[PDB]
Length: 51
Length: 51
Image (cartoon, rainbow over all chains, first blue to last red):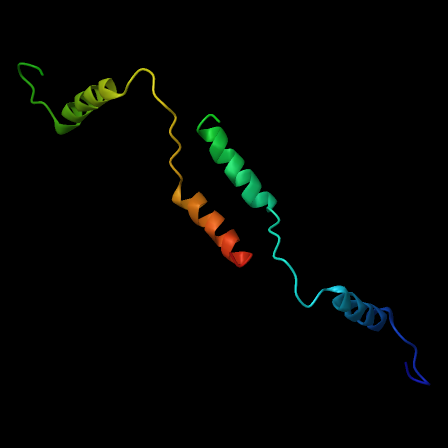
């Protein structure tokens, strides 16, 4: 913020991003989330062998 | 084979294909062979989550 200026939505969002970065724990578990591209690729192969 | 003709390698191969078709059992197990494209796609995702 500047005495003569006017704050923009972009600066407000980048500051909000730093707040969300603090919510991220310094150490976290690498819990694997199955991607849809991988999920369906496996399902297609399983259906190819009739399973 | 024809009295005036001469057999070609293509006809001999198509006849050999029928012999190999007889080796295929009428009923068989759908044993799934993991494709390289699927094998590496899974390995890439596992390495992406650090595993």
